[PDB]
Image: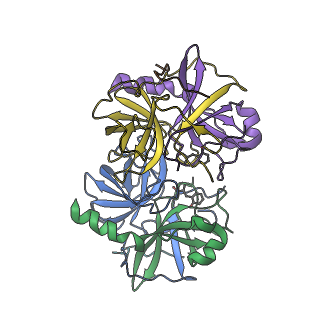
Chain colours: A blue, B cyan, C green, D yellow, E purple, F brown
């Protein structure tokens, strides 16, 4: 996020951080419930990566975060690698997230749901803050 | 869903 | 990357005014937002684009792509959860 | 490949084409032997995709191609998603490729191997031919 | 995409003359080639960059990235198999 | 390895 501000700790309980055996954060994900995360297709998540929730400060050891394993990667089949059209991957967790004051589900909309232009939204993550 | 325990601040 | 989680508010746009920018790259299952002085960026992907709808944050989009440079002028481009919730609804029934 | 020419059929027997349950070709791969392919990390290969060898014309039904399943995706752990540095993924096949006049291994070099500038090489695949 | 397999010859460059183009995006495990009038492009990735060495084609690079537009002027950027064969050599021993 | 059965043509 270039030009964003630090969040309030645990105020976005659905945010996951996907990290490789290395501990490297490379993509964000979202909790739709306690057995399944949603991130992007391009991310390219494998079952050797770990889903991390409850995190706030990637660099803190004293933070009671949850490191979740991936059972199955479910890439949409309408996913268009050359286009980046339909860039949704589901992740099925081998071990259930424990819901708490800092781990919760986001709401999914209706196919029907309308979300109109000039509407003020909010995006989060642990992305380059500078280019 | 979508209602956190810790309310986000902007 | 930053160590601790960041957040930015940004206005969603129509795809049309977005085409003004991204052209025929903008597809129907894709939804633009920003060009507000904030920019999603490397490492942001997979992540949440939420909106407030009748008390709750709803998953409205998924950071997917945009500027090579993360320009606060170019709108970012996210997944359009509305065009895909049908499939999500469905993987879960199944597994 | 923008400005390239049609290859001779089966003259690059190590070329694989990675395709999704859909039949959609989205990346190329290379045969290093009969149980393992090498493609890119970014590709984002899952074990629900299929490795296809012996193909030449993606659109031909009469071509004796081999559709291979993926046992395990092995992404390098030095892979840098934000950089695209170290963008090598190995694929371990569940069922062995059958080597033939059209399916063969490419040679891997020495860490030592030198490959100097202004040297004429060749790249192949089934990529946009026009932009 | 084309239906049947294409091929192009292209000259490899030093990373340095490549930096002239890609800057600090060029990393040591990355190796440029073209800007010859040929261009690797969408769908090409994962794929082979071969060179002739003492009878045999050797895996010298892996199409990874470059031009948004697939410019025959910008050099493409491939994986540098030399900086990674050590790891390859190793996954196989193991599995 | 690296020596095909069908020789590539350029
Ligand atoms: C890497 C990325 C998103 C991105 C990059 C650059 C500019 C904008 C943007 O949304 C995801 O994953
Ligand atoms: C998508 C891609 C490679 C690529 C795209 C654009 C321009 C150059 C290039 O090597 C792979 O996979």
- The location of residue A102, given as percent across then percent down, is 36, 65
Q: Determine if residue A4 is in view.
A: no
The vertical placement of A94 against C7, above or below, is above
Q: Quadrant of residue D54?
A: top left
- The location of residue C93, given as percent across then percent down, is 22, 66
The vertical placement of D52 against C71, above or below, is above
Outermost residue, bottom side: C54
Q: Determine if residue D37 is in view.
A: yes
How many labels sit on residues? 0
- Which quadrant holds the N terminus of chain D? top right
A90 left or right of E5 in image: left
In front of the other: D112 or A33 = D112
Q: Quadrant of residue D102?
A: top left
Q: Quadrant of residue E9?
A: top right
In front of the other: D121 or C93 = D121
Residue positioned 59% across, 46% down in the render: E41
Outermost residue, left side: C94
């Amino acid at each position: 996020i270039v030009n964003g501000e630090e969040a309030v700790p645990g105020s976005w309980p659905w945010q996951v951080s996907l990290q490789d055996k290395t501990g490297f954060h490379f993509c964000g994900g979202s909790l739709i419930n306690e057995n399944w995360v949603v991130t992007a297709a391009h991310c390219g998540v494998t079952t050797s990566d770990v889903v991390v929730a409850g995190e706030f400060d990637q660099g803190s050891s004293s933070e009671k975060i949850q490191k979740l394993k991936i059972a199955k990667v479910f890439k949409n089949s309408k996913y268009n690698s050359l286009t980046i059209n339909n860039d949704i991957t589901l992740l099925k967790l081998s071990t259930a997230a424990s819901f708490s004051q800092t781990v919760s589900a986001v709401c999914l909309p209706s196919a029907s749901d309308d979300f109109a232009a000039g509407t003020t939204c909010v995006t989060t993550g642990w992305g380059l803050t500078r280019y | 869903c979508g209602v956190p325990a810790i309310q986000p601040v902007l | 990357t930053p160590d601790r989680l960041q957040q930015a508010s940004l206005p969603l746009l129509s795809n049309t005014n977005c085409k003004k920018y991204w052209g025929t790259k903008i597809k129907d299952a894709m939804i633009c937002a920003g060009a507000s002085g904030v920019s999603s960026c490397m490492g942001d992907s997979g992540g949440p684009l939420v909106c407030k709808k009748n008390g709750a944050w709803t998953l409205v989009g998924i950071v997917s792509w945009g500027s090579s440079t993360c320009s606060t002028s170019t709108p970012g481009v996210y997944a359009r959860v509305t065009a895909l919730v049908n499939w999500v609804q469905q993987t879960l029934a199944a597994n």
